[PDB]
Amino acid sequence: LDHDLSVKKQELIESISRKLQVLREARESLLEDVQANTVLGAEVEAIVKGVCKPSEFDKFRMFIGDLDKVVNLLLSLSGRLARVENALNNLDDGASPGDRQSLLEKQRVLIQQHEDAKELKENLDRRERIVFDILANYLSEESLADYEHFVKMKSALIIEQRELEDKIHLGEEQLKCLLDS
Amino acid sequence: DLDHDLSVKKQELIESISRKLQVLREARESLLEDVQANTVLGAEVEAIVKGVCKPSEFDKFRMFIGDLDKVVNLLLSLSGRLARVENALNRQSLLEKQRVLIQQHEDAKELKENLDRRERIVFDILANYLSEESLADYEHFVKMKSALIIEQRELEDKIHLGEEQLKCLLD
Amino acid sequence: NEGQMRELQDQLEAEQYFSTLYKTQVKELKEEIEEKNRENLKKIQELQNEKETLATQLDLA
Amino acid sequence: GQMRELQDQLEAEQYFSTLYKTQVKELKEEIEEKNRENLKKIQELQNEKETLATQ
Ligand SMILES: [Cl-]
Ligand SMILES: [Cl-]
Image (cartoon, rainbow over all chains, first blue to last red):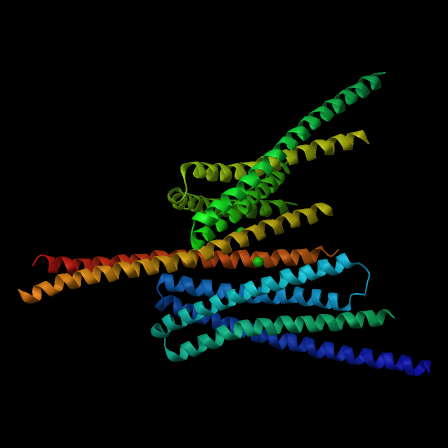
């Protein structure tokens, strides 16, 4: 029976390794995509500098910077919240009650921070509609479509990248732990 | 046999530090009486404002007081670490930390400015609502708290250091 | 290293205080904007009504 | 070893401080602009009331 088990281990290892390979390829392709979207962004910025007065442009650049920062914030924050959540879940029964209470407190503070970040998302969207309405008058419709596509693509693409990175990291971890056997 | 000379020099030094440390502890106790009395007085002022003042203006008052502790303690922790890194001169990674630290210090200065603004506003709104005596109690209370946390932290740092050297030398 | 730990803890305290103070300030700012907006609205209502009382006089003469 | 998590917390509160600061800026600029516009309008209508007053 030992043969069956060993070959089973080998099968699993090979499969997981394949998944890791395909995910890496996806990392490369997606990186090409981020490069392209970045170039489109630079183009939009160039076009807007000409038509937009200095205040409008400062609100624009400030807006995008705050976008990147906001997204990364929500992803890191949601990350720690998920980790603490799974820790509390799989935590052994009994052990220490003060530990369960401290972890619950971490859950509380993280969820509150999440609400604050939510309000921040609302305000940032307000800013987005503000810049959208102001810039709609200044620029053409085609370049405008390219702009909107770009802005949405930046955030969505950043998230896609980070989630993928998490998956590949995890797969690599389970693979390593399994090979150690 | 100058080893004797050195040993007695130590013994004298440690004795001195023990004395000064005692003085600092007693002074800390008196300061503790002061913080308690001032805190109860604070509760009283809060009650009077609760009765006489409006809910909104009262809310800005609570905002002000809550923000006060945070501002003061912030400047004390910030000035503390800044002194730690500046004294740390007595592979150049630190220079960047110094930069961010001074920038944070300027930002905190701006925050102090706004807090002082709010202090003037709460003072103006409260002068009309309250008596001159109760007003004296309010001003005395706010300034007493602000200065008092600083004094407390300074003393606590001093004593903590004295204990550090006493223990370190005493083996 | 423990000095790194403690130093980072102090940093966290700092940025916490920063965030909190900026939050309270933003709130007081929004409340202040609504208050001044409202009071000013009142003022323009008064002024326009006084200009109306002044306007009705010219009609007769 | 788990201090890197604490570093993550610090990064989070950094983002907080930055975003709230930027928001405060846009708010201050917003109050100065809006106040300026109000001053303009009230000045205008006051001037109309003055031209009417000379009658
Ligand atoms: Cl928060
Ligand atoms: Cl800062």
